[PDB]
Structure formats: C-alpha cells, structure tokens
Length: 123
Ligand SMILES: O=C(O)c1cc(-c2ccc(C(=S)NCc3ccc(-c4ccc(C(=O)O)o4)cc3)cc2)n(-c2ccc(Cl)c(Cl)c2)n1
Image 1 (cartoon, rainbow, N blue to C red):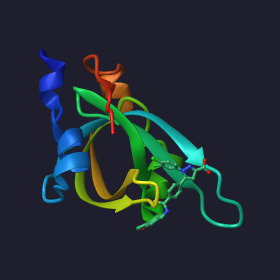
Image 2: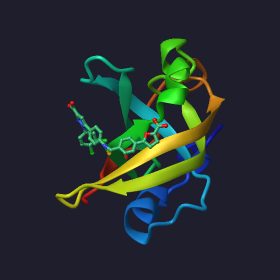
Image 3: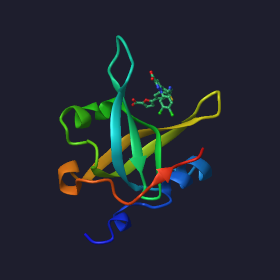
C-alpha cells in the first residue's frame, strides 16, 4: 500500500552493523540474490538487502534455508521478516550477517519493484 517504504524496517541495517543488535526482527526487502562459489559443498547464497534507507550486500543465507531460493519463494523484490540472525566479523573487520530464520511476508511478484531509493551502507 501507499508509502511503500513504511513497510520496511528503516534503520535496521545500521542497527545491525553498528549496535550489534540481534533481538530485532526487521522487515527487509531482497534486492538481489547470487550464489557464492563453494565447490564440493551445498551452495551458499549471498543477498543484497534493503531496509528502505540503505542497501547492504553482506548477508548470507543459512544453508537450511536454501530451498526457499531454489523453489523461488525467496527472490528479488520479496519482502521478508528476519526472525533469527547472527553477525560474524572477519579478520579484516568486515561483518557478515547470517540469516537463520526468515519469513516471506510478500512474494516478489506481489511487490514487483525496489521500494524507495535506498543507498549503499558505508561500513
Ligand atoms: O566466493 C566468494 O565470492 C565469496 C565467499 C564469501 C564468504 C565470506 C565469508 C564467509 C563466512 S562469514 N565464513 C564463516 C561462516 C560461514 C557460515 C556460518 C554459518 C553459521 C550458521 C550457518 C548455517 O546454518 O548455514 O552458517 C558461520 C561462519 C563465507 C563466504 N564471500 C563474501 C565476501 C564478503 C561478504 Cl560481505 C560476504 Cl556476505 C560474502 N564471497
């Protein structure tokens, strides 16, 4: 409905990446999904997500959620609620958000466009 960015948890990306907040259950839009190079192991999916203010590509899906991508329930433009996630910090200082539980609130086909004009998060 009208004011589409009002459907997303504006400010959640900054909160996750800076405050270390893990209790929140933010609503985010998937902008893009791409497989990461793996080899002899299940694929892993990396996501460019939006909270309506920022985009951030430092999300990965827990492999238990792979069927959501492979059966096309989780795809570009869908709106999702993150019910459980963890944050990992790499040796170089970058942070990665591993999505453990999520719910698709609106399918990609029911949304159909990138919501708002989010700008890349500066980590
Ligand atoms: O090839 C490539 O092109 C490639 C590769 C990677 C990549 C980078 C980091 C890792 C991590 S953070 N290694 C530790 C880890 C992995 C899974 C877990 C876990 C906890 C529960 C589960 C589960 O249930 O599945 O998995 C925990 C620690 C992995 C790949 N990336 C990459 C680079 C930069 C960013 Cl910002 C991102 Cl998001 C990905 N690109």
